[PDB]
Image 1 (cartoon, rainbow, N blue to C red):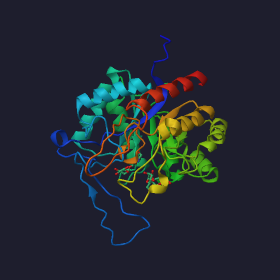
Image 2: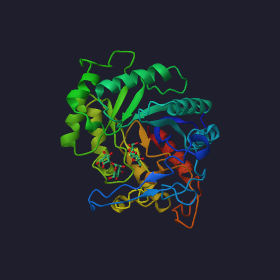
Image 3: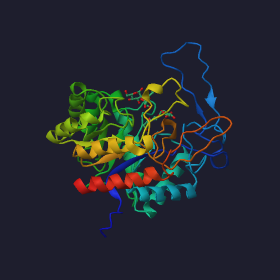
Image 4: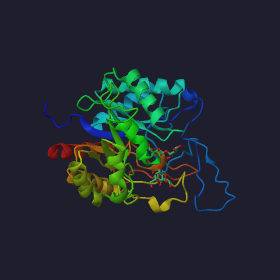
Length: 349
Ligand SMILES: OC[C@H]1O[C@H](O[C@H]2[C@@H](O)[C@H](O)[C@@H](CO)O[C@H]2O)[C@@H](O)[C@@H](O)[C@@H]1O
Ligand SMILES: OC[C@H]1CNC[C@@H](O[C@H]2O[C@H](CO)[C@@H](O)[C@H](O)[C@H]2O)[C@@H]1O
């Protein structure tokens, strides 16, 4: 078929499965959330928490689906249909090494639901406690062993792919042991080889040698807020792609529709980026496409805490809070606008 409605399998959308309901999970997990203290504020801070009631959830926006459980099969089915609408072929699943049965259950449900709609799943490996190259290898082995035969498990030209959040917290001399073909615990030329995509944060002076010396296969930028880092400043993307191509690396810029996290980080107003009826999203996605990259990542499907979500949101005013919403656009606008940009991306690919 050549209808311009097909999934794009070089488009990765960052997905969070940490939401709960009292009924399914025992608590409205993540809808309730601690308010972060000000890193530059007083020493006697009692910031408190967001209770995660119907009236007061840990987001500046409000989900169309309500305080949903990420364990709810019917929520998962709706999410996969939303992925189909957005034409986002790859769900990049947050992964925190929780080693508990409820997470294992969610991962299986997600894979199954994804496959029903021909969506693929890869893992976004987060900075879990004591993360290091040895337990990363062990966890990569576990994930590939457990899920590698699942039909929804993502592969690019035969290789799995992982995004590694805050990869800079691990020294290149450690990374090399895992990622150099010569490394003492290398995954290269093994059953566990994978495209490893590290987080490009700061200036080329620092990041270029880091990426080369760590032997990452590529890099992404994550942050939805333009200018938050050098990597998340879209005017740098042409130059970043040039370097990537010169050095055999895969550049996967992250684009987002906006940013606001002030419910959970009330001191962090400087990072707010307004959606302005979709123009912000358009500007950022346009920059990614114009940079001539082979793959794009979307921050995010449902990071509701950070207000970067493309998942449908609805207008809501409670006695506790007046939520932001999609303004002059319909709840599914960011899904359909994503499909539009996926089309433009494919057009120039
Ligand atoms: O200050 C809150 C800040 O937290 C996150 O970013 C973290 C870290 O993960 C990241 O590597 C660096 C990049 O400079 O910033 C840290 O403080 C993230 O949630 C961000 O959006 C937020 O503003
Ligand atoms: O997925 C990468 C990145 C995206 N932003 C959130 C990061 O996690 C951190 O912040 C959230 C709230 O936004 C907290 O709930 C987490 O505990 C914290 O680690 C995440 O790593």
